[PDB]
Amino acid sequence: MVTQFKTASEFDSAIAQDKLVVVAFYATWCGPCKMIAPMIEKFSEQYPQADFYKLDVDELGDVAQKNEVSAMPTLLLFKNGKEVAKVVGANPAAIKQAIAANA
């Protein structure tokens, strides 16, 4: 299970963690948003040592802007308040390799 955010504060809080946080940022009205649902869940399914969070821009658009996510679906990895990876497309293997790389 990938944990749900509530506000940009939640996003930022997960960001400030001294560990790999990969955020599943998509929109419920978007097409391939449903690819980020299981693919990203599958990431921490392998390595739960990383932080799994997700949020819909449909619900929180100002949050999207806070994170620099306009495209969807988007994956944002951060460490300790700074980025580590920015992706705008579910890439099953390459992004699982990403999360592990930035971790």
Image: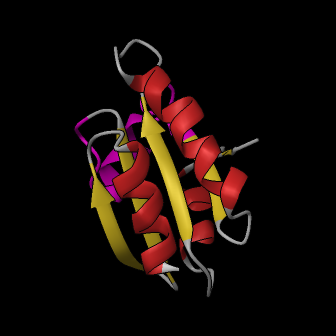
Image point (62%, 70%), residue name: 13
Residue 1 in picture, x, y percent from top left? 76, 41
**Taking 12 as reference, is 44 above or below it?**
above
Residue 30 in picture, x, y percent from top left? 35, 16
Q: Nearer the viewer, residue 30 or 41?
A: 41
Image point (23%, 37%), residue name: 71
Residue 86 in picture, x, y percent from top left? 29, 61
Residue 58 visible somewhere in the drawing: no
Residue 25 visible somewhere in the drawing: yes
Q: Nearer the viewer, residue 65 or 3?
A: 3
Side of 45 relative to 31 (left or right): right
The image quadrant that residue 48 belongs to is bottom right
Residue placed furthest toward the front: 93
Q: Nearer the viewer, residue 95 or 19?
A: 95
Q: Nearer the viewer, residue 70 or 21?
A: 21
Residue 28 in picture, x, y percent from top left? 47, 17
Q: Give the colour scheme shown.
A: secondary structure
Side of 22 relative to 42 (left or right): left
Image point (34%, 14%), residue name: 31
**Taking 99 as reference, is 63 above or below it?**
above
The image quadrant that residue 6 belongs to is top right
**Number of numbered labels in the structure image:** 0
Side of 23 relative to 98 (left or right): right
Span colored in magenta: 55-71
Q: Is residue 70 magenta?
A: yes
Q: Is residue 48 magenta?
A: no
